[PDB]
Image (cartoon, rainbow, N blue to C red; front, side):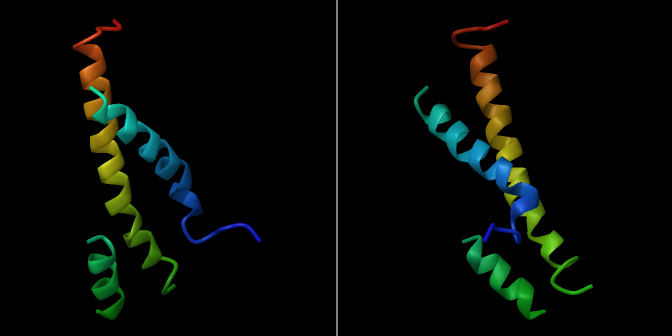
Length: 74
């Protein structure tokens, strides 16, 4: 009934979408599909999750950067 195939990173997904929309106001399927081609589907599923995490990390870092400069909160 509930999703559990992306649940360890879903919070970061939602938090990524909103942060990108607040960032702009101031492919991945084609990589995961051959990754399946070349225990299993548990640890292998844990190799998809770096891709979608590093993008969020970059996004929130740039978001906080253009908050610390340019309407400087600190």
